[PDB]
Every structure is written in structure tokens, then in C-alpha cells.
Image: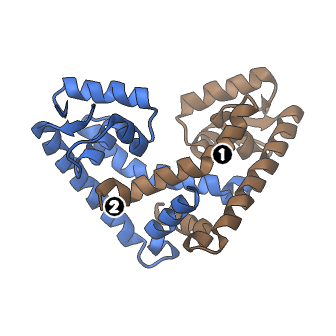
Chain colours: A brown, B blue
């Protein structure tokens, strides 16, 4: 067949797009942007994060990430942790919202993993885990 | 560990981003933009192609794609086949050949590094995931 159709980078990028599409539809409906949800997703377990780590987890440039975090701050979702390497945490409202979104994310993920269970892709998660490990 | 740690969409997005970042730097060097590279990639193996299909394969919204293709045209990399179908010019082709060669070299190093691992069949896994998602 053709180059693109079998190219690893294409297959990765298309997958991530198509797999994310439905959940991103949901975020959009909630009036939220994808980067905003990712910040929420990162902060749900952790108590506080440096904007620089938030950027790396969210796959964004530092400054774009901070424009976003500032907006969430203004809205009351997120706050700066006081100090004497700044860190950022969910507010209560932030934490409520993150929690209900992470719930949806998980259910949507389970829907998909189920659909994959019979197939070749059943262990997609370890596979990708392996990939990132190698890519390090 | 944490939620994001094991969350499939993160695992997909981060993989894709990390696998690409390697190659996406070379592209930057040859003085290209990611969507231009993608157009060259699509057109290396095909004679003509619709802008709709180009956009599809490149994960681009169609009008952004059409702007970009049209600028490539102005720069002499791509031309319309005399119904709108785009093909590479000789120059575009020399450039595609060159970048796709790099792509296939990077790809080989990656897949080679995966051959000892669970991830050895990654391409098949992904093409299955894609087939389910349709």
C-alpha cells in the first residue's frame, strides 16, 4: 500500500485523534477547552504542580500553558500555592469539576477498552507504556 | 501511579508527541511546517490527490489545508492537475523524496528499538484500534 497508511507516526497521530474525538466532544459541550481539561486531569490526584510539569504532561509550550493556567485562575478553578518554581493547585470548585470529568474520562476509556478486549489491540496500554519507556 | 499515568488518551497523545518530536525537528531544519511535510508525505506515493483527502490524512481542517496547499503551489512545490487534484512538482518531489527518506530512517530506528519488547507489533495494534474506531 502507500507510505502514509503504514507510517508509524501517522498511525500514532491518527489513533490519538480518533480515540480522543468522542471525549473531546464532551469537553467542548461542557464549555471547556482541551488544554483546560488536561490541567484538570493532571491536578486531580496531585496536590500541587509546577507549571513546567503541567506543560510537559499537557504537551504544551510553557508560555501557552501559563496563559491557560492564568485563565483558569481568573475563573476560580486553579490557584497558586504560596511560597518564600511556582506551583499550582485546584480550588474546591476546580476539584469538583475535575472529579466529575475524570469520572467521565474513565467510563469512556472503559467503553473503548472493552471494545478492544477481543482484539489485537487488547493490550494497547502496555504497548504504549513500553513505547514511551523506549522513547526515553 | 496517578490517573494521567495510566489513562489511555494520555498514553496515545504522549506517544504520538514523543515519537514525532524526534522527526519534527528535522522538518524544522529543511524549513518546512508540519502540515507541509504531511502533504509531501501523502503525495510521494500518489500521482494526484484531492485537497479533501489531503486534509483527512493530515488531520487538518479543510480550509486551513487549502490555504497551505495553495501557498505550496505559489512556492512551486505542488501543482493542480489539469475537478481539483494536486500533485507534486519536480521540486516538490525532490523535497518529498528527501524527507520521506528521513521519515523512513527515523521510523526504522524506532521500530528496531521496539523489536525486543511488548511494543514490537505496535503498527498492527494501532491499525486494529483504528479499525475498531470506525
Q: Which label belongs to residue A22?
A: 1
Q: Residues within 10 Å of mark 1 (few under 14, many from 20)?
A: few
> As displayed, is residue B130 above or below residue A18?
below
Q: Decide if residue A17 is on the left or right side of residue A77.
A: left
Helix, strand or loop for disc 2: helix
Q: Decide if residue B120 is on the left or right side of residue A54.
A: left
Q: Which label belongs to residue A135?
A: none
Q: Which residue is mark 2?
A: B107
The residue mark sitting in front, 2 or 1, is 1
Q: Position of residue B108 (x, y in %)?
A: 31, 65
Name the residue rendered at 85%, 39% in the picture.
A95
Residue lying at the far bottom of the rendered structure: B116
CA distance for labels 2 and 1: 29 Å
Q: Which chain contains the residue that carries disc 1?
A: A
Q: In which quadrant of the rendered view does residue A5 lie?
A: bottom left
Name the residue rendered at 41%, 48% in the picture.
B21
Name the residue rendered at 64%, 36% in the picture.
A34
Q: How many marks?
A: 2
Helix, strand or loop for disc 1: helix
In this rendered view, identify the residue nearer to me: A103 or A131: A103
Residue lying at the far left of the rendered structure: B90
In this rendered view, identify the residue nearer to me: B106 or A3: A3
Q: In which quadrant of the rendered view does residue B123 lie?
A: bottom left
Name the residue rendered at 34%, 53% in the picture.
A4
Can residue B1 be seen at all in this image of the molecule? no
Check if mark 2 and mark 1 are on a common chain. Answer: no
Q: Position of residue B9 (x, y in %)?
A: 62, 53
Amino acid at each position: 500500500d502507500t507510505f502514509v497508511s503504514g507510517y508509524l507516526l501517522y498511525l500514532l497521530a491518527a489513533s490519538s485523534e480518533e480515540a480522543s474525538a468522542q471525549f473531546h466532544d464532551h469537553i467542548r459541550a461542557q464549555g471547556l477547552r482541551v488544554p483546560e481539561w488536561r490541567v484538570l486531569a493532571c491536578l486531580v490526584d496531585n496536590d500541587a504542580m509546577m507549571i513546567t510539569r503541567l506543560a510537559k504532561l499537557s504537551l504544551m509550550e510553557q508560555s501557552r500553558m501559563t496563559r491557560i493556567v492564568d485563565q483558569m485562575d481568573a475563573r476560580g478553578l486553579v490557584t497558586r500555592v504560596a511560597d518564600a518554581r511556582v506551583r499550582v493547585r485546584l480550588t474546591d470548585d476546580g476539584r469538583a469539576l475535575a472529579e466529575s470529568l475524570v469520572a467521565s474520562a474513565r467510563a469512556h476509556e472503559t467503553r473503548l477498552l472493552s471494545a478492544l478486549a477481543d482484539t489485537d489491540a487488547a493490550r494497547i496500554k502496555g504497548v504504549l507504556r513500553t513505547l514511551l519507556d523506549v522513547l526515553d
